[PDB]
Length: 375
Image (tube, rainbow, N blue to C red; front, side, top):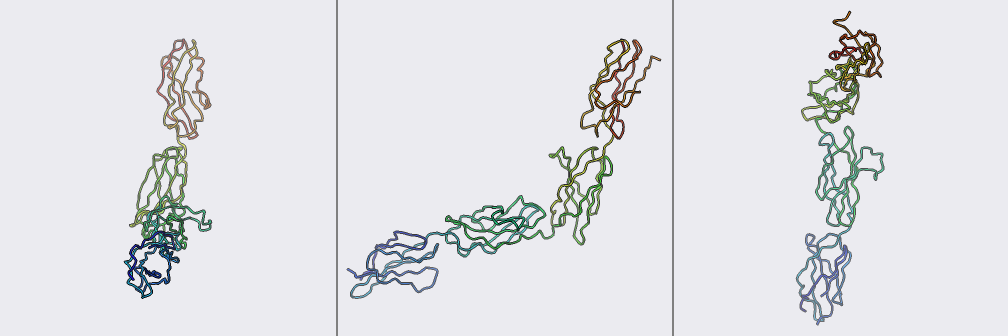
């Protein structure tokens, strides 16, 4: 007989293909192109429709039909192409690997799974700093169909665990075995025994243990004032086990982090430590000093405390000194006073008056004198 010609693919699933097209019956012969030469055979198809089952998902096959009658068989028809449908992956990604790119960025790489069962639409990377955490408590990072990715915002100084799974449009596949991410080769370790010692109101000496047999090139110290989180400082210096910071502001809380740089870059910073500088004497006088004579022998002096940034400590007391140039000292004034009444002055007499602020360390500078005459 002549081969059938109207061979048409009518339905396609993940594991089955339905085909439709004077003979007695038909035979359906099929092989996958990239496989072995010998075809598989389905014999005795008495109708013009049939559904071939048992196929593998996401696999390309070739189909052809020949006709047979009472005389014998005939040549096969032209071959037609077909690709089975998708399923969820059945194998995890292969050769998963990871390493630290920076102090907080890791690079992850892998190979496609051996059994994707479809077109991969992306991957899901699960990672945790504590392997004791349950698997579903890990952080999930989704990627596209690429075979590598980066994850930032990691916590520094810790070794992560990781495993990746693939998913098609159907669902997720199994996750790979857990792997451990590698470390930067020549990058130094987080400094150990990092301490801060208050030396004075302007000096703080930092100390730590120098790492043994480690190609340290220089240390990087980053510090800032707690009240000025936006403004930070950084000083680099030759390798040592101690460093004294100088010229700091008195009565100021400072925060510190330390890192180590080798020829291969800087390591992870220490956690933040804190220290407050000691107090000093005030560096500015009270502001807005005014003097008024309410009577013939009384003068009222008014002032406001120095600006907060120049007190260098808690103001503990005030002192008033006076001296008359033409005519013939009260300390221990409590910190809550904003005015004090000078009594017993001479009529129509000019005095020189200075106002002064104090900390526990001592007195600061006094304001420029304000002149006032009684009566």
